[PDB]
Image (cartoon, rainbow over all chains, first blue to last red; front, side, top):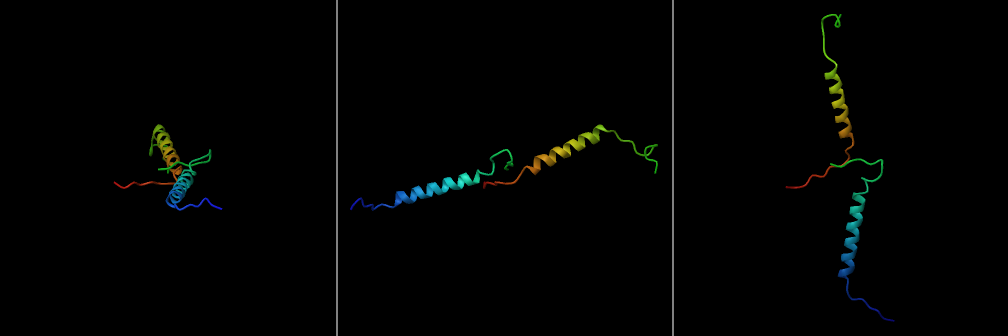
Length: 40
Length: 40
């Protein structure tokens, strides 16, 4: 019956931060495990 | 021809070192799968 939200910038900032963290984790996912290669 | 008689005469340490260097170069290069070139 209430609790209205009129702000959207923090949500977009958090979404962008989560996307950047996921991209970083996917980029560093290659060099992991005993069967991994090296980067140049 | 005869070769071993008096034609060609080469040592073995040079060939061993060359083979070891070639193996090390083939090992240190095959473990590469990504390159990151930064802009100056």
